[PDB]
Image 1 (cartoon, rainbow, N blue to C red):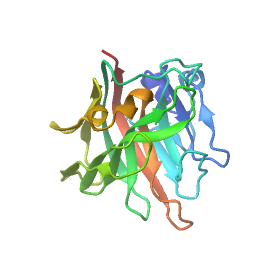
Image 2 (image 1 turned 60 degrees about the vertical axis):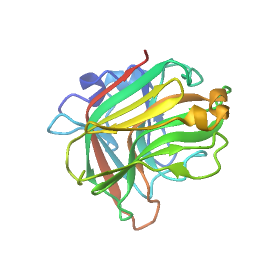
Image 3 (image 1 turned 180 degrees about the horizontal axis):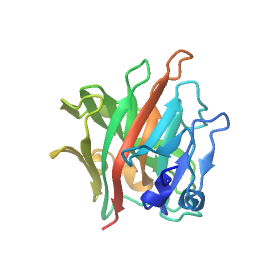
Image 4 (image 1 turned 90 degrees about the horizontal axis):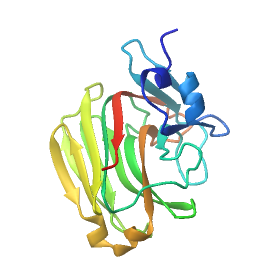
Length: 227
């Protein structure tokens, strides 16, 4: 077998969340030993790949199944996360190869978290459909209300894309393929100062129907920078 993704990529600052029955989480340490399964594997082109089925497990603060990386500043403490001040950036290149029957998955996020580690809302969701990418940014830190929608066209099922998600001083900057949009989330609602944040990338499958099928998403590069 080809080298597992945590041998190819530096995953020392991520944990992996799975769409198995008991929604399992593989620590950074285990990713580093070379964890691989039907959910997470190195494909023949080298890509780090998710398979998640729509009938998979979903946990307490998720309506849908995922095979997805969750950023761990401190591999042993998921309460260590970053905030609105300074600069925090994820860059990745990827492709979505298979969709569920909904035709929709999420391929990257910035998720909110409370200081005590409890559930908070998502801040940025990279919503992938064949030929429609919506980098949605939440407006209300309490989790009510609608998102600012940011639409990019022409990115097809199977196309390689380049993505950046940066937060600088409470402004979110969302970029597909050199097209950057921004949303001043901390200027829209000072409550965002009271929350912390971490990155996510992989396959969060927006379909939980019994007949939904499964989704495959790939990453060829993934890095996080905290200026």
